Image: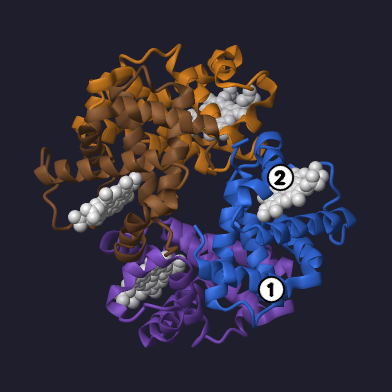
Chain colours: A blue, B purple, C brown, D orange
């Protein structure tokens, strides 16, 4: 459960990401594929080489979805219901993998936005990504 | 476990870590981001806010010892379960630190390295450090 | 996130517990102390011997709280805010321990109510206890 | 790990387990309660509802083999990491089963034993079985 302070923190941080959200999404996916190679088993038909245009386009989709999760942070089950259908019903992604991509996103934000990534923001972002992860892995519709 | 090129990567970056500061920044963030870990450090004094935690002298002095032990691990990457044997005893026998927490500290340390080195903490370098902090977390679990 | 079917399941099952909720709460605590002895470190001033009256009284309090969580399953953060203050702010219970007591409660319900504990109900109860656990371990107020 | 009185408890109850049924009931509940585990059994056919899962013949036949291996573990409680070595290879090399899932199946099996034996699955008996299923989960993790 997010505090009201957590929500202000996440809105402010993600706002700073801005028009770089695509490139950050792509970098986080590349970090997750390289550090945790079992995650590649969910993307068999993808080209997952470095600089792949499929990863670049997927990273953009993942980022746009998080932007939308941020704008509906009070009503996330309802704003993410189609992604949830895809991740929990169709793909059956093991919940452990959400912890992995969450970590790779925090690492990406720490490397690129060091002044924004204070301990208070780090703590809010971490709670936000856990809550997004819980909605994506639950069948509730 | 590590490739000779991975070991060289891990070593080169570690030569540039401030060993007076990074250990504290990591222990500090662990207490702020996963607040139940504050229970194990009740004797350290004021941990009431993030600014309090990050400025606590005792958190800084203890983070130095934690980072000292990670350094000893990087010097004995082939024999981690021996380097950390006394230390596994202590975290299990005297405290009972649930081993999930060791994995959380390792991941906070990777974020702090990312934060300090920026574009130099490339995906290949991160993937080498993930292997080292998983190594250390496993040798601590008792 | 609970489905609407999950909520019907939990209400019906817990309803069957009835006036035995106290004795079930106490049995679950005794199972958790015996199977996972590190959990005793949170109760230093308790008598934790078998048949202890302190465990019996605590088991009753834990059960009454779950009854209330069930009756406010749509608004749990608000119905459990004082327990959350106690578990997350004051006691700092490590979240791993909530998985342990959740398992000991499922085992207690399986041993006593075998006809109610079908696979569908088991799945709903498990999701309910994870959601109660997430509210108790979060600082959001 | 187990006390001589714990080993006797674990053995006596296991003599009364239906070995044609319990393995299936456990694998069945794993797929219903933690539905992402259905990904590893796509070849088994219809897993669309709980009634479908619990009636699937292939789930029943596979649960028999899982319970067979738990039985082999209870006969070699002192040498679990040897009994399960081939089996750790298979779950990691061919499938990649995240080791958290091994802990989930062990806990579903304890619930199914509770369900079958009722008041005979006392807290002391449960505490002996928790030690055996943690044992088995750890020897499978690769
Ligand atoms: C914050 C976490 C995540 C977000 C926001 C997210 C978001 C998305 C989005 C927006 C899509 C594409 C939806 C569409 O085009 O219809 C997608 C597809 C997908 N996601 Fe995720 N995802 C996340 C985590 C994960 C993780 C952890 C995995 C696996 C390790 C995963 C595997 C997939 C796969 C396999 C696809 C389908 C790709 C394709 O078939 O083209 N996702 N995700
Ligand atoms: C994961 C890597 C970790 C390493 C390398 C590490 C290392 C250390 C070291 C070197 C000491 C001091 C040993 C001594 O002076 O004799 C220590 C003590 C301690 N550690 Fe850790 N530790 C780790 C994780 C954790 C975690 C996750 C917790 C708690 C959540 C924790 C809680 C403690 C506590 C309470 C002490 C005793 C401190 C005191 O009494 O002042 N450690 N650890
Ligand atoms: C569903 C999970 C849980 C529920 C519903 C629950 C509920 C409660 C309730 C109602 C109280 C007493 C509140 C009061 O009298 O003011 C309480 C106190 C407490 N709980 Fe929990 N609890 C749960 C899980 C846990 C777990 C997992 C632990 C530790 C392993 C724990 C440790 C405690 C302690 C130490 C107290 C204080 C006892 C005392 O000081 O007298 N609780 N809990
Ligand atoms: C925890 C105790 C477990 C034991 C004792 C166990 C035991 C077994 C055994 C005996 C086999 C068949 C080996 C053979 O015939 O050569 C097997 C296969 C398999 N297990 Fe497990 N297993 C366990 C957990 C899991 C878990 C948690 C999963 C997935 C979530 C899983 C997925 C599989 C799959 C997919 C196969 C191959 C089945 C097939 O190809 O039809 N197992 N396991």
Please state if D60 lies on the left or on the right of A115 as rendered: left
Image quarter in which the C terminus of chain C is found: bottom left
Question: Decide: marks 1, 2 in contact (CB < 8 A)?
Answer: no
Q: Which subunit holds the residue at mark 2?
A: A
Note whether B109 is above or below D39 in the view shown. below
Q: Do the residues marked 1 and 2 share a common chain?
A: no
Expressed as whole percent of the image width and height from the top left, the position of residue C58 reads 19, 46
Secondary structure type for disc 2: helix
Q: Residue C127: tell me if it is visible.
A: yes
Residue density around tag 1, few if under 14, some if 14–19, many if 20 or more, within 10 Å: some
Secondary structure type for disc 1: helix
Quarter location, residue B59: bottom left
Residue D129, label in figure: none
* Residue depicted at 61% across the width and 63% down the height: B130
* Residue depicted at 65% across the width and 39% down the height: A88
Expressed as whole percent of the image width and height from the top left, the position of residue B49 reads 41, 78
Note whether B27 is above or below C23 in the view shown. below
Residue density around tag 2, few if under 14, some if 14–19, many if 20 or more, within 10 Å: some
Expressed as whole percent of the image width and height from the top left, the position of residue B85 reads 38, 63
> Can you tell me whether the CB of the residue at mark 2 lies under 8 Å from the nearest atom of ligand 1?
yes
Note whether C37 is above or below C6 in the view shown. below
Please state if A129 lies on the left or on the right of B83 as rendered: right
Q: Nearer the viewer, mark 1 or mark 2?
A: 2
Most foreground residue, B87 or C74:
C74
The CA span between labels 1 and 2 is 38 Å
Residue A83, label in figure: 2
Which residue is identified by label 1? B9
Q: Residue A37: tell me if it is visible.
A: no
Expressed as whole percent of the image width and height from the top left, the position of residue C71 reads 38, 39
Most foreground residue, C55 or D122:
C55
Most foreground residue, A129 or D3:
A129
């Amino acid at each position: 459960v997010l505090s009201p302070a957590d929500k202000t923190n996440v809105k402010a941080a993600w706002g700073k990401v801005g028009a770089h959200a695509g490139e950050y999404g792509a970098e986080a996916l590349e970090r997750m594929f390289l550090s945790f190679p079992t995650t590649k088993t969910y993307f068999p038909h993808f080209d997952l080489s470095h600089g792949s245009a499929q990863v670049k386009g997927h990273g953009k989709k993942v980022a746009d979805a998080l932007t939308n999760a941020v704008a509906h942070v009070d009503d996330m089950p309802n704003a993410l219901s189609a992604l949830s259908d895809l991740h929990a019903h169709k793909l059956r992604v093991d919940p452990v993998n959400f912890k992995l991509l969450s970590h790779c996103l925090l690492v990406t934000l720490a490397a690129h936005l060091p002044a924004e990534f204070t301990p208070a923001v780090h703590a809010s972002l971490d709670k936000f990504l856990a809550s997004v992860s819980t909605v994506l892995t639950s069948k509730y519709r | 476990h590590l490739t000779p090129e991975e070991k060289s990567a891990v070593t080169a970056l570690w030569g540039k870590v401030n060993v007076d500061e990074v250990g504290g920044e990591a222990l500090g963030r662990l207490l702020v981001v996963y607040p139940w870990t504050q229970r194990f450090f009740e004797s350290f004094g004021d941990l009431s806010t993030p600014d309090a935690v990050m400025g606590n002298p005792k958190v800084k002095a203890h983070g130095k010892k934690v980072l000292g032990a990670f350094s000893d691990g990087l010097a004995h990457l082939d024999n981690l379960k021996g380097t950390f044997a006394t230390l596994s005893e202590l975290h299990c026998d005297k405290l009972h630190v649930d081993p999930e927490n060791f994995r959380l500290l390792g991941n906070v340390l990777v974020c702090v390295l990312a934060h300090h080195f920026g574009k130099e903490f490339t995906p290949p370098v991160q993937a080498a450090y993930q292997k080292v902090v998983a190594g250390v977390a496993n040798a601590l679990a008792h």
